[PDB]
Image (cartoon, rainbow over all chains, first blue to last red; front, side, top):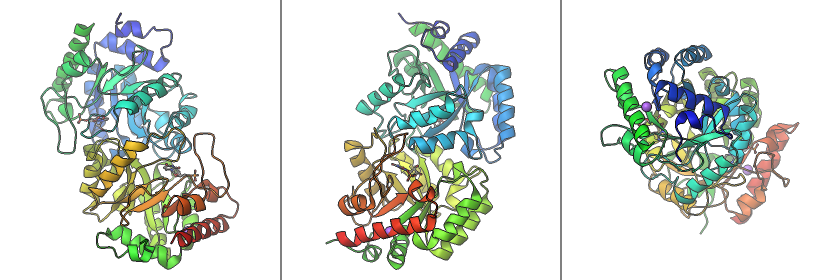
Length: 256
Length: 256
Ligand SMILES: O=c1ccn([C@@H]2O[C@H](COP(=O)(O)O)[C@@H](O)[C@H]2O)c(=O)[nH]1
Ligand SMILES: O=c1ccn([C@@H]2O[C@H](COP(=O)(O)O)[C@@H](O)[C@H]2O)c(=O)[nH]1
Ligand code: NA
Ligand code: NA
């Protein structure tokens, strides 16, 4: 029935980026994505180096990096290759296809040049994916579609979520999975990544809501936890990352 | 019943940014927003200078400007003040509140420092607005909510559109209107801006769909047309802008 990450990495219809990710998840016993929500390049790189062994993925918001340069991203790639994790820019492309292709390839960030994965909202219709994939397919990249959100009042529910699943499953040459709160596709080739995760109950004062790794991986069937402040705001970010890694990994093993 | 732009600028509940815009629209007889979808700063600035007298607003995507600097945006502000138009960064904020506040204030673009207006998708729930307004209210800025999209397969329909209207009307200290294809709010204090506009029928090969100024302003009741390629790709962008300005202005007068 359910397959391990290592077996999912071999599925006939697996995308190469998903396969690479699934293999390193199994090798390293990690299904943790660090949300590296910092404004300094030095802190980003120090976190990537120290936490690299503990993570399958590092998620960026490079538009909050006060001292972004392309050379910072070259350094990040070196760490990603060393420690074996993917880089996911959480850009939330959400425009018409003709615009998003330029936002993905160009400008000062040149996201496609360094991000293994990006994500998109499905609200514009499938042209958002078609535009991205024109840049992403030649660059051998993957994309995640936002099927659900963690925040209070999210409209990514019901028929909207179903539309995201259909759009992913119809663009499988580029779309490798979802941002979601739970398993939303029954096809094991697709990844499920879940933000809004902390060990303790709570939220923030701007609509964020938290659930635990056991809830999201174990009871809701997601694959990967995305954790920002639960790690970033801790004193010892390495031990915090290890606590989240162990939590998510055991929840995965026990559902398997 | 229906009020002119100049009278709407005086409504009791008008936002100061909306009032400023409405007054210059009436003064200059323009309800045209140029979508300055170019990758070179020199072309952006040359368009802003030449077309400034013809437009009420210049819409940017600064993340496609290959040679962005904050000094480019200082030059753009000088032109906006000279010719009297607002600057609208079409960033489509679409994250949780805690993230979007940092994307609006910070990073290399420092959007809030130069953009009169920004926009947001409503899919995350109202925390997206609450996060933005924490930066935007002290900086005396305004925001547009994306209630409908012009592209094929858009999911911004039905209950989603109604949720966008409610979210705007409940955050009127910061939200001044909508991106929409038609009038969606019955409250005249809110602006309606409509992309997907060309004089001729057609679309693009990535899901864009076009309607004419007479259709969108006259028959659908919107306030402002947003025009990119219909102007940008023309040989004489000034005459193209004048054709779109005259079309949108007459459609407004005839519905009034
Ligand atoms: O539905 C979503 C989609 C994305 N994020 C992102 O995931 C991270 C959550 O951070 P934290 O709340 O763990 O600090 C942030 O970067 C945020 O932008 C969410 O929180 N919820
Ligand atoms: O529903 C929407 C929202 C925004 N835009 C933006 O408006 C402009 C349309 O350009 P064009 O098709 O007139 O060239 C682009 O910058 C695009 O990103 C749309 O086209 N449709
Ligand atoms: Na883990
Ligand atoms: Na006009």
